[PDB]
Length: 243
Image (spheres, rainbow, N blue to C red):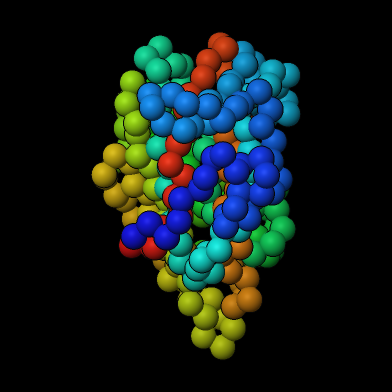
């Protein structure tokens, strides 16, 4: 079940056993909200990617003690005050495979990523950057342009207002046969108790390229940035056994 929980009071000083670095708090801050220790994620009007001038969200990287390189789940809760405008979606974060680019319109032969995005009206999708020059049998799973979305129909308006939404994302490596990846990797997403699973993934090209870190980086879009100054709260970041 839950292997460990991030202590947000250590987020800017190494994260304890989560081995956090790469921290960019931007305008966000660890605080208390609804009696929980949370991060208030501050999204300025017109914030998003670096193509957008406002400041929004926050980021950090973690390699927790106990990270299982073959399969692992990360989980968190998020509160959207009534009135929050989800626009046309944005990122939370997720699990990165191997080393090298796998996000931001850039791919690599050795890296992949499995992330949560929100969508319009509070939807959720699994958003995957697969590696360059690696066979996939899942239709549309190609390492070109932006990442590939899954579960569009399955989490429509899943993210509700004025409550703690529970989100999880699980990642399980493919196996290898004589160094050949076997198109048997998996992903799953859970939102407020509903689980959807994706099988038949090649997550890497070689048995030394495995699950390597959790990268958190929340922001609107691209391409559509935050329509207004607004906040959301994140809490209870957990690393969990892959179910």
